[PDB]
Length: 216
Length: 218
Image (cartoon, rainbow over all chains, first blue to last red; front, side):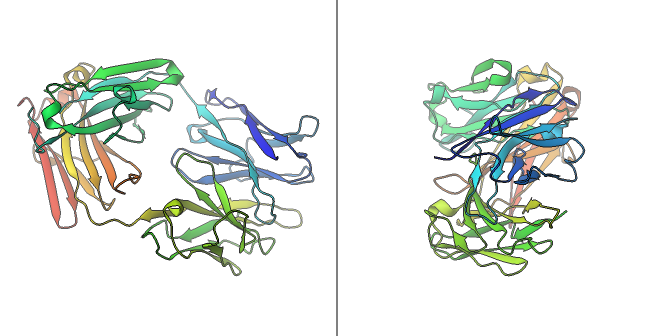
């Protein structure tokens, strides 16, 4: 069994450095060439560099500034070190033998690197629905504002309400903080009786918010 | 350096339809077969489906087939299946005797084809709790609609807002293949309390649906 596991990753303050190891098992790290790729949130795959079988680095234009792709045969690792990190560098970094002109292609699972200026838990405000104006169906939700970094997960009634839930992708507000909404459609007749609570969880700040959403 | 570009950025086909995605390379790939096709689902790592331009990997369904020639490369899905709707990247390797480089395409979403469905539009006033912090958020919800394309305009006292809204869109729902969209208008409490009528105008095709509220009437 061949395997490629990725080490390192986490919160890095801007200008700081990320160091990511890529540990192989079932084969030797010096018998193939290896790339580092990254995928920003919602964006496409972006090649960073490629270390040939001969230990020769081939960085990219934007990467040649602050990127060193080394290899350690003692520990069976290929390493990526980036300096001078910007907000555009927050992404999921993979290591891989891309497999363009070879039958052997292997990828790591990907480790997340987040460039954070501050850690800020979210503020949760109700999206209140009674006076419902959509017949027998009402909409309600939770507005999750001003948090950093990603991600937040949202459930409803501790996961007992999943039908009709729409949790939107976060957007980066001009203030530099993330925000998102989670909505759900419910019987407008159930508003006075059924309880609706959104469970917002922000692990980077160890914060969890449960918000009862009531009419008016 | 090199770059890849595919066709199109997004498409819509049916279960059993014949899908064709092309891919153009900036230069000639170093090795002739240095072209692979990657299938990536949301929240999942990329999965290589085809290497060596035309060679399928073991386990890959034979309905997939790559037919590249020079700098034009095609991914063919004979009978499109439910598990084939995803984003497809092409990746090419091109360097020299003293160079070795890759570049990915931009991607191509193979979306489900769906009959037109109008959105259920809801508007949400800012909560009183938020207003105490100095900022007002007005949210407009477009629930379970198709197609994705839609014009959402904010009006404050019949004055079209510009540059103070942000949109977010879900992926296609796994049951009805619809989209949901939110538009969030951001104002200060001072500006929010200066006006009365807040309206969200949703336009797609020949129809415009406007949901609104008066600040204070509940």
